[PDB]
Image (spheres, coloured by chain):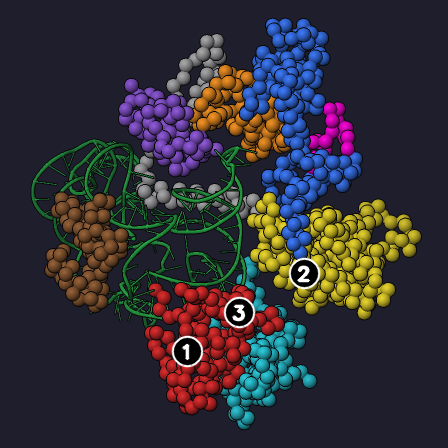
Amino acid sequence: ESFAQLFEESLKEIETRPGSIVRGVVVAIDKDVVLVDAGLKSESAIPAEQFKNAQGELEIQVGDEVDVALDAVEDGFGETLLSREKAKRHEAWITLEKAYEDAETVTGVINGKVKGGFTVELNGIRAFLPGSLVDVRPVRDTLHLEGKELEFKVIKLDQKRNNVVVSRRAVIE
Amino acid sequence: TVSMRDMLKAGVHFGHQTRYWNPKMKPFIFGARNKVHIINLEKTVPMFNEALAELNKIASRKGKILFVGTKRAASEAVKDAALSCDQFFVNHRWLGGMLTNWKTVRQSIKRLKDLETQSQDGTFDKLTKKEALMRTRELEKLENSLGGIKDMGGLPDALFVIDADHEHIAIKEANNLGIPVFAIVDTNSDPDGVDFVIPGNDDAIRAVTLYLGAVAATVREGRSQ
Amino acid sequence: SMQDPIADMLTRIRNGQAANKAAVTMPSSKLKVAIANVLKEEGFIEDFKVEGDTKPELELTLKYFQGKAVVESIQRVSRPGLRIYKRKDELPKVMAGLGIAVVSTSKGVMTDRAARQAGLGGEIICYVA
Amino acid sequence: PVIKVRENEPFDVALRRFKRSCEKAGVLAEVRRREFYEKPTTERKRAKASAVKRHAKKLARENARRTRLY
Amino acid sequence: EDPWVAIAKRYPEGTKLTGRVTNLTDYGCFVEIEEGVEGLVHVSEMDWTNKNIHPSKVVNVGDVVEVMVLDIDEERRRISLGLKQ
Amino acid sequence: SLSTEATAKIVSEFGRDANDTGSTEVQVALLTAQINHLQGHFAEHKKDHHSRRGLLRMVSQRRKLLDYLKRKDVARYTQLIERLGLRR
Amino acid sequence: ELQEKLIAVNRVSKTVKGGRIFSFTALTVVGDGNGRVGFGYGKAREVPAAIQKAMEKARRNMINVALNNGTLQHPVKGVHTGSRVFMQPASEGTGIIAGGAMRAVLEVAGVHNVLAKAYGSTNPINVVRATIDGLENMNSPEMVAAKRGKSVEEIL
Amino acid sequence: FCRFTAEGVQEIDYKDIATLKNYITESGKIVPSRITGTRAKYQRQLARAIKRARYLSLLPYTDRHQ
RNA sequence: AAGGCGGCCCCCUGGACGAAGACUGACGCUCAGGUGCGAAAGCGUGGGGAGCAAACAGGAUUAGAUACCCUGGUAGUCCACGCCGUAAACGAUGUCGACUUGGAGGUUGUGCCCUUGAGGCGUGGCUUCCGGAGCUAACGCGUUAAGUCGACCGCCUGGGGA
């Protein structure tokens, strides 16, 4: 009745556009295609490569839930943009968390600068930062044991274009 | 028989994007959420029920049902549905003029049957390796094409379809013949050829399965009756 | 410019019939209203409804039997360019009596048969079949 | 396309850069265009024709793409 | 407005970047990440074979890679990145 | 075009209410003034054909208005044509 | 019970590397002497085969026509391509006053009494089609009554 | 991705030379609205401004000339 | 309005569209004769003349080459004021009004919305492409009709001769 109208605005209320609400249950796996169903018009053709973690093999069987992304609808047949970007928002949230206590702490390990800032990698992803950010002072991680364990202390981020240079070693600082 | 909540869960209410719609599906559409068309479940359900009833009735008079779905996502499922109620199906590409040109296709069917017999019942073996291979290939081809309809004998007395726009050839053939059509018709599709239109999501797998299952059940019921 | 309102109305009706429109709205006029009434009486439309005070809108509700439209044909006969007046003996028979011919007579607008019965002819507005 | 060879820059690299600059400018193309007089009509025709071609490439081909080749 | 006034940050000759590719247009790959810009890495570098390469075979779709500028025009917004480095 | 102030003045004089503006007579007056203004322009610029088209149109409109006035109410028309000095 | 009239047979050519390949088209029409009519257009390298094909075609895809006794129910126009056709019901005894292809279709249909002119083109195939269309569209009194929500005596 | 829509400028200024300089070539030419992604309405204005500047010797007509 | 109109600045000037209101109160549509505007070439008188270039000249090419190609080159193209009144002056589609499924754009307004951002939801004008019903000999046209109608005008009646 208006049961359906109310149900429609209800279902509007219990979804959003980006990859935010972890809703798609993995309902068929086959190499090399994962597929979910986050309450969209169709199922995603997911790559396998948005879902293997840091050494190459899969992590999620049937029933498992990751949100994907949206705002792009119908290229002919199908639904989404990939859930891996989803993950980027989570990374952004952790980076943002720094602001609260003026110190985000994880592990950052930066061996070298492709473009003037050591590369830092957090969990699966690896990011590039401007040259200063890698070291607090002039210490330089070239003399440090290769691909060393610290955290990342942030030196510089570009806030629009995503480049983040983070602070290896020197826990005291 | 099939509830609204279940349908919703499945994802029947979802349709195609607004730019790909057909304006003949404007009655069956409710609204457009996130630039994607939403099918009206209030109008869908009764129609669906009616269709089911019709199917049951057909079954009751010993009607032959044909299940068509060549999407390749729900090819596995449609076959299963067909087999549950021991009815016929076309899960791979519909041969142009399967029904209209039955008399030619009946020869093909016969050939296929013969091949099968040779493979299984004969137990002769001792065949030239290339020739044998060729034969096998032929058999495979036939099975893929006409596996479900090999025991159909004549023409079916009704035609269930998973997508109207995709299987338009089949639908057209049915129309030409005068076989009742029971099509699942998304917002992009054309409902004019279809007798018993079912407004619903052709694309989503779970929805398709749901559509199949109820139909199968109804057929079984009819048979029992 | 708008020169023939009745004709326009007829055209609108025809288009509605073609396009499977449930109801057809237009600016109201007395003659138009009369015509609508006549049609209703003869059973080509379901109902008509005028609505408004300053500029009222006549809304006809079209009829559909077994899918297809009821008003199979609907032509103006008299028209501003060239008027048609018939005497009671010269009054036509549309579709050999199965259709109707709206004719405006001294005793109001009526179907051709009605006019004949009365014993009077007049301006032939439109054939409807 | 004015260019200056940077300190300790190779010749070949410089040449390449120059070429790139020229390309960007569209100088050669411009020269080619102004070699002979194009009637206005002809110019119009080319522009419209080209546009049409572009449109064809964009949409019709896209439609084709939807359907698989084999 | 926003990327193009002070386009001197990743400029100077060879500043390496990490950028996700977007669409490979059979002459190109279109890696573009740094806050609303467009890069190409077209077909000539990409590898250490020139012409027979077909970029869809050789890298990816949607993947963050090794790329640096090699060239900026801040005027006809064509930053022409590379990948053979 | 005719300057706003001038237009207002014209309206006030000929219009009964002064807020009216659309009175036939007022309209005619407005047209007439514009025509007068454009005469000067067109003496100077004889080849300005496009502009002259507009003037012609305006004139036609004025004529039409006058005609309308005549059939409706003769005395008023007469008065108007005395005021403006329109030969017809 | 069904009567079948071959209206026309026409030789049609296809030019090939060698020369001209000829073939034959047969236009037939069949009817049961009541409402049911159907035309068929068959084609083959030899005439008889073509005719047979046409007949076969005709026999399927027939069409019903409401006939008030021996004649039509009202004057009816029918058009198809060039051929535009007028046919008018007529009094018992008058016979089928109609020309060519048109006549044949009428005869099979079991109209006995018509006044029928073919305006425009008289290309048999088109004209027969036109005639068929005309017949098809033609509604009966009962049908009209049903449509309009009235009795037959209200319509007269 | 137009700048002038976002800034929300009423009219582009020929005096604002720096801004103009982003939309002009290394060779002096005005840059296409495909490349810059400038809105059509604004683009024309920008062009006009550039032209004005060139007249006032604020911008150069071309790189070579002297 | 069509013909057409392209650096920048100023002066004079015509139209279009939107936003709300306020006013006038059918004043409208179409138009035989009539009047005007009307590319290019062309004409007249007076200026101008860089480039380009009918004509013309030479050099090639060729069987010939009163052409194509090359080297030159005068009317003309440019300006002023007159005349000419035609073009595949084409959308080969008269003007005005009404009505009839859709999609993807472009351009130019304008209302609301947290512009939380380049956006979101509308609503007007002009415009490019695709396509439905319908129409069409077919090709195709398809809310900018070649659909469904009304008003007025123009025009056609076998090819040639013309």
The colour one sees for chain C in the rendered image is: red
Quarter residue G129 falls in: bottom right
Q: Is residue E15 left or right of residue E5?
A: right
Subunit bearing disc 1 = C
- Chain I: its colour in the image is green
Colour given to chain E in the rendered image:
orange
Q: The chain coloured cyan carries which letter? A: G
Front in this rendered view, residue H64 or E54:
H64
The part of the chain drawn in magenta is: A46-60
Amino acid at the residue labelled 3: Thr
Q: Nearer the viewer, mark 3 or mark 1?
A: 3
Mark closer to the observer (3, 2): 3
> Are the residues at dot 3 and dot 1 in contact (C-beta closer than 8 Å)?
no
Residue under circle 3? C61
Q: Can the viewer see residue B151?
A: no
Q: Colour of chain A?
A: blue
Chain letter of the purple region = H
Task: Tell me the number on the disc at residue B197.
Answer: 2
**In this picture, residue I38 sits left or right of residue C63:** left
Chain letter of the brown region: F
Magenta stretch: dominant secondary structure: loop
Q: Residues within 10 Å of mark 2 (few under 14, many from 20)?
A: many
Amino acid at circle 2: Val
Distance of mark 1 from mark 2, alpha carbons? Answer: 42 Å
Q: CA distance from mark 3 to mark 2?
A: 26 Å
Q: Which chain shows up in yellow?
A: B
The residue labelled by disc 1 is C125
Residue I15 screen position, x and y as percent: 28, 50
